[PDB]
Image: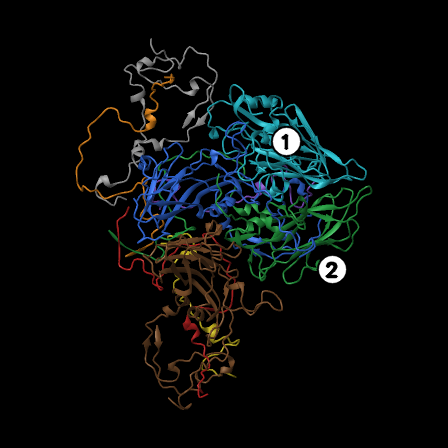
Chain colours: A brown, B blue, D cyan, E green, F red, G orange, H purple, I yellow
Amino acid sequence: TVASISSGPKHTQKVPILTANETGATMPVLPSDSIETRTTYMHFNGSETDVECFLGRAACVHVTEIQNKDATGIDNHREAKLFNDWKINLSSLVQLRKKLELFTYVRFDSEYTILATASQPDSANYSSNLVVQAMYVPPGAPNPKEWDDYTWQSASNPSVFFKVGDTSRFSVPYVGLASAYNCFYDGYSHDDAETQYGITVLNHMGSMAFRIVNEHDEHKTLVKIRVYHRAKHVEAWIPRAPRALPYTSIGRTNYPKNTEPVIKKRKGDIKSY
Amino acid sequence: TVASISSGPKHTQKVPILTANETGATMPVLPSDSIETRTTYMHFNGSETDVECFLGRAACVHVTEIQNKDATGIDNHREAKLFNDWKINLSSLVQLRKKLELFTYVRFDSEYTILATASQPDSANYSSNLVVQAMYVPPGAPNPKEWDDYTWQSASNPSVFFKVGDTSRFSVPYVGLASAYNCFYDGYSHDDAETQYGITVLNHMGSMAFRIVNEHDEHKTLVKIRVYHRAKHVEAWIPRAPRALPYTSIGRTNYPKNTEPVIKKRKGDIKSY
Amino acid sequence: TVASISSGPKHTQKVPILTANETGATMPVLPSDSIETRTTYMHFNGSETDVECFLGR
Amino acid sequence: GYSDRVQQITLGNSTITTQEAANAVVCYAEWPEYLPDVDASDVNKTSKPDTSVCRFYTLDSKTWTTGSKGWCWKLPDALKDMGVFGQNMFFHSLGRSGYTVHVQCNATKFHSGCLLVVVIPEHQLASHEGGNVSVKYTFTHPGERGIDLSSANEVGGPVKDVLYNMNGTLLGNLLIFPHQFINLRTNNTATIVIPYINSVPIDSMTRHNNVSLMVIPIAPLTVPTGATPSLPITVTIAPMCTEFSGIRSKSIVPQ
Amino acid sequence: GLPTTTLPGSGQFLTTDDRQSPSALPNYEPTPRIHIPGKVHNLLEIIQVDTLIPMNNTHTKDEVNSYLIPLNANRQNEQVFGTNLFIGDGVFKTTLLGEIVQYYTHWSGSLRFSLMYTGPALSSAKLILAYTPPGARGPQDRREAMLGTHVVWDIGLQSTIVMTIPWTSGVQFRYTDPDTYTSAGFLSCWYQTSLILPPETTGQVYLLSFISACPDFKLRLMKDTQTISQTVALTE
Amino acid sequence: GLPTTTLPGSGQFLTTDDRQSPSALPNYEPTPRIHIPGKVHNLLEIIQVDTLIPMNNTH
Amino acid sequence: GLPTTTLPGSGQFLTTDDRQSPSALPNYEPTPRIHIPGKVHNLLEIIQVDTLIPMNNTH
Amino acid sequence: INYYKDAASTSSAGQSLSMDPSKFTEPVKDLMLKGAPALN
Amino acid sequence: INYYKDAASTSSAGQSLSMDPSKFTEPVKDLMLKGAPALN
Amino acid sequence: INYYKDAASTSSAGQSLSMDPSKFTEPVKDLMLKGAPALN
């Protein structure tokens, strides 16, 4: 492939460099339309800019935490972090979010990796070996109420059991209700006067509940869960302007008030170098 | 495959929507018999509603517990949870049970996964590493009496040894005596006036005994066993009405007295939306 | 493989059920030598009684 | 001029005619047939009394009134005493059978009411006590009398609550079982052909019933003005393709 | 010895994975299968059988009576019943259809709603059933109702009427657990002319109503049902 | 049983590796794709569209 | 290095499984078999020989 | 590839792709045609 | 070699090697030739 | 596939499928036919 062809002096009536940008086109002008060039080859394919590659590496999408401790006398397991749920999202930690929102609709399978590490912040004789249970709870399933409910039987709901310190990995097909996930949605769920704007089920990817299977030892053990997400089989439509201001909320476009100028001011003139 | 064909106005003597339900049939009426439709395709196969898929994921079927402790002076190992048996069942935890009882007779191979985790509720210097032994004890075999009987030699009886914290997995062929397992049985074992009703060997799947192989350390260690069961190679006959009331017993259909209305009462009229 | 063949009434001079055990043999008598039977198949091979299986765990 | 409506069933030495039928149901779309060799296990030749057992027995009649809750019969129990069918039953170790069930209830074009006639394979009943109380033998072997769902709880008997099918499932879903309605305005009989359904090729006829026939009023009986407020319901049932095997001494059963 | 590397996920137990395992009972021979009528292969086979809907939900304890929709003689213009179409909740919820839908997260497809009339044979009636697609409110009078999917039913010799709720939807799947964006409409029924009883007859007549799914239907993404739970393991 | 040896790196999680995984939802059927104008395949496709430069940065 | 994943059950010992193992005595030559009357192959062969029943159990 | 000798040890079965609701939805003895009158 | 049955479980996809910026860079209704005048 | 060199290291043997009870059930010198008299 040639990156530049050889081209010499020109004295024409045919001027490729004068255009009318009002038309909305970006005319494909090249170095050889306005200087004299020599042949050179590309030596490159643009492999690593493919959208499959761009969205295809694992990104941290969620960090939560649960603890193993005596539940005796706990009136609210959920509240003691005896167990914890997470409604899956890709817009809570901003790194991956800005990447996805370069597109309007996106379609892909997900590969999840879940790393779990334990901490024992206060005096323990040892490090126990805990098994985590991660249950995938689709909308309409009974939700766990205690850390050892009938729910955890999970007879119809996919669940994975792995050890703290290890990693669990499985992949979920594209679960969207429509043909693509909406990265944006300028609508409501119905014509209600007060219903929420922008947040939609069109994006919904399920939800996940974590708990330790082990009963309690004498000390307490903090287990912190990190969920990583990798898109595989990516398809993206309609590019948009990149995110400039900071994010404030999952699912709305809102930016913070009295934010700071995002364009760097010159130290000098327009004329400055 | 078409999900709907195109159909237009009708003014006939041939009315597919008038039927006589007294006959016991559900006549196969479609949208296109009563409105004007356009062609649309199915795009779907009904893969995930196959009975193999429906009964084919692991469900928790049993949680038991045994402990490793000094048996010195214990007059009844079984009673100290020095070891423990389980007569295999699929009707003790209700999630999987309701699923199976959608059918009258069911035939399948079982794949068991056994997760074992340890707990040390009171002061230990460390976490020991225990090996569990799970013995499959078919009816007629000597049953363990102490946690270290000749029984555990298990020279003819399949047994698996795995480590606490790990998982054991093996699969047992369909061990039923008849051609299928009866999910229901309106009979007795003989014409006795007082014999039990409903519970039958027709369902019997063996039985399993667990123990720790390790002798005792200075502290005590609680090991809690969870048995998961996955049906593979499923065959199901005669669908029945789903279970509406709560369950009270393994193997009987009995529901609790002064149970609550299972049909949700309207907040409003018959006419309400 | 048939487990039992069909067999009907008998009024013979040929009695397979009378033997002399003093000989040391176990004569291969079947249900169909003394009652009327219907055909049935074995559906079974005797796999799990092979000595390799019996001593092999 | 054949209508779905008029029918004749002749079985043995007995015939039934209905001039107001609503087709007939054949459970699971299968018609009763004898036991094939490929499916056989017991080596015994079986006995097939044919026409002496495969005829129509009419059980004693019931009375539908505005307060009726529904009735339940078990098979082969209901026939345990009918003619030679019954003798064969007590005298062989094993037996097998399919049936034609014909439920009858006629009224006039001013009455309203609708019965559900359903056959439930393996209808294991529940104890009204809850827990794991069993349902004694006698209670699940009412004989030709059947069980009257509007009778009182008894001790060792089953629960008789209709919205729960006597087992913890809702009346509304009984329609997944082969069934037919008798709607006075349409229908006057219900006919169901039952093939033999079991997990073994042949079984005991006394320790295990393999279907319960259930007739349940759903739209209450409403008679014309100053009419007598009730109608009789009659059940006639015929064993079909019956086979008995393992003859001997004659079973003795509780009560 | 062949060199290997183990990946993330090694040793995990995923209840939904499908792999081979050693048999604990090597060489065992299972009982032969015999023939049994009634084999089920897909849950899609059974949700096409219709079952009764307790439409008359207005009672206070479960009763046979909540299956009966009453009809009044001589009323004109008025409304017989109304319900939204959240098949996973409300009237639908205990029906076989409702009961199976609850094992899955998403559904799509047409529904078949039929009404069987049980009044005396010498009576007569004309009813209108209307399906209102998502976007409008439950109709408030027949005029409103008749502008959407509807069938004038003429009560005759043929006792049942089968109305189809054709799949009307932007999004190709809806949630089985009730959700707004994903909502399916309303179903109402009104007198078209009116029920008329013959002489010597009196009182209310009832309609029975059934629901089953068209062959159109799709259910996906299995999950656990809210319809069953427990607090301690059962025993024998 | 086939003899194996595990190499350095076993058990590591590299966010950039690309391997197979079990599907948590065996047999599930995704929604059909419909046509949507605008598909992007390479970031190289979009950086050829011109956009305005805030050249007058002096504010 | 070929990528692998280990499944549930790894490391378990099931007394009934049947796999290959290294021989501790590589290259050893067993004694030749000679003929011996009486070989049994199935327990089904022997349960067809009749034996006496202590029917008179009353002692 | 099966690594094991017994059939019980193989993975899940593969979709019936059988599907025939008529044993449940139309178990009537005389065939009913949609469009023809239910009761003649 | 796929070891798994479902398509979601396969590794990353492989390069589009599609690449056609004209839907974005030249969505004009009447075709513009470089070198010819923009507005005639 | 055997991974090992020695025969002892291979898995269990496979069913004789030999089966001949006559060495045990009928070791008589002169052949006895069922149905013919035992002692002539």
Task: Decide if residue E236 is on the left or right side of residue B122.
Answer: right
Is residue A57 rendered to the left or right of residue D204? left
Which numbered disc, 1 or 2, marks the residue closer to the eye?
1
**Residue B118 shows in the view:** yes
x then y, percent, for residue F58 = 44, 88
Q: Which mark is residue D146?
A: 1
Left or right of G41 in this view: D135 = right
Q: Quadrant of the N terminus of chain D?
A: top right
Pointer 1 local density, CA inside 10 Å: few below 14, some 14–19, many at least 20: many
Q: Is residue D218 above or below residue B188?
A: below
Kindly identify which chain the residue marked by label 1 belongs to: D
Q: Amino acid at mark 1?
A: Gly
Indicate which disc residue E143 carries. Answer: 2
In this view of the protein, which residue sits in the foreground, D98 or A210? A210
Q: Position of residue E201 (x, y in %)?
A: 80, 42
Tell which of B54 and D138 is nearer to you: D138
Most foreground residue, B144 or D195: B144
Q: Is residue B204 above or below residue A273?
A: above
* Residue F50 location (% of width, % of height): 45, 79
Give the Cα separation between the discs numbered 1 and 2.
52 Å
Q: Can you tell which quarter of the image residue E3 is in?
A: bottom left
Q: Characterize the local packing of mark 2: few (<14), some (14-19) or many (20 or more) Cα atoms within 10 angstroms.
A: few
